[PDB]
Amino acid sequence: FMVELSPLRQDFVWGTATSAYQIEGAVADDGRLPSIWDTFCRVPGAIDNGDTGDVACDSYHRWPEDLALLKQLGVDAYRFSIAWPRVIPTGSGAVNTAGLDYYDRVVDDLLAEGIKPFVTLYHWDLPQALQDLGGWDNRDTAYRFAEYAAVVGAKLGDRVRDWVTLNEPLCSAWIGHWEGRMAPGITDPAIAVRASYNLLLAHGLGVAALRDACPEPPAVGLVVNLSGCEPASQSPEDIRAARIADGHINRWWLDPTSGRGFPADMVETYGVELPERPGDLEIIAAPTDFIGLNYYFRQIIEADGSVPVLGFSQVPGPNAEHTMIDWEVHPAGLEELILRLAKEYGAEKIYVTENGSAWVDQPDAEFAVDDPDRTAYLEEHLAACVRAVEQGAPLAGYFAWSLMDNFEWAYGYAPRFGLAYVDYPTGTRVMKTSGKRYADLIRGHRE
Image 1 (cartoon, rainbow, N blue to C red):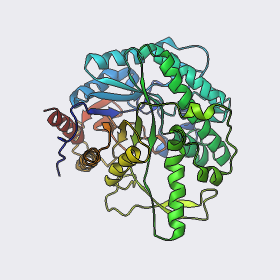
Image 2 (image 1 turned 30 degrees about the vertical axis):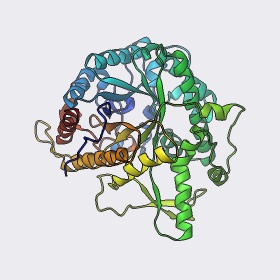
Image 3 (image 1 turned 135 degrees about the horizontal axis):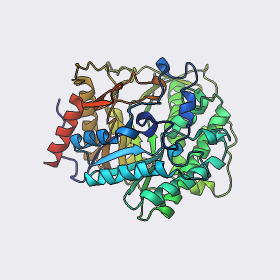
């Protein structure tokens, strides 16, 4: 199968994405202080194989090697994140000049190569100093986030025009504070629900901070990892359970940012008093210029009385094709979610801010990798994007996760998502077949 991209407008944005803790390393260099992910990597058992982000791809010191990959791809845009503890290391007060200078240089270099920066402010690396004050269960953290947004926007917002406040708040809130599988490893539904609230408040305060501080008017959006939630059977119980999952995974984030309040069925499900103050709903519903869809899989849901509060469990998806971390391959789910954002939520501009897959790579001695399953996943999901556009969706671009292999959180380095292979001992990056195919597809679209 070879995807046909001609239905996409010529001003479609072709991109690829990374995040700071996953690639930068240099965790103690040039004024950086620890994040909650530094701390989590010191907890025995938290990360598969005892991996850490201490070195990762060493992109703090090897940024030109990333830029070389970006030029080889011919992407129009690069989505990367700013490390809060590199810029305001304690989360309050003093700005770390050297840290902010790094990102200033990245922006200039990208623009010199004709590549637009898409900047994520928060990609999970909360300063540990703020976690020591209660983290996202302290409303003050949202105001610290807004201050950080204003610092970064004032510095970069003459050149950076495209901004993400938070990446995947579901992961920060539910996986970081309910499941405990991501930093800070808390397992408490009440803390988790309050954290989800303060995260959404931080999003809204951050939108306002960027519009106030950027020298040129910013386009700002939230990034959410959505999954269609489908019942394992047509029993009334499974249908209802899948709808609760839909609230937990999708509507909890989309409804209040769209001005529809928090979904009443989920408020009743959680039974947690939201830490709400007058005016907060208007802040959370701050007007945005796009919505960022991260998509990897749908979720098949069954009713499950053994799961406290939620009463549902994910079960395996039925498609034969699964990635190395057992994520079902289902490109139709990407088409469907793009259309749901356009139709049900009236989204005026949608980006696929992440999509990609991890497979076992077999490099040769010079790190060349032929990755046919990663390539096929890419082509099939691009075809789903094309179908959504043909049905009227305002899809403005697509960002491949990821530019190169990197630290995949509690999985460690085992799942390689890169379009380019990374030899971690040397930092050598070598484009895989998938990345070369992506470059060919971009070129063919522009021709």
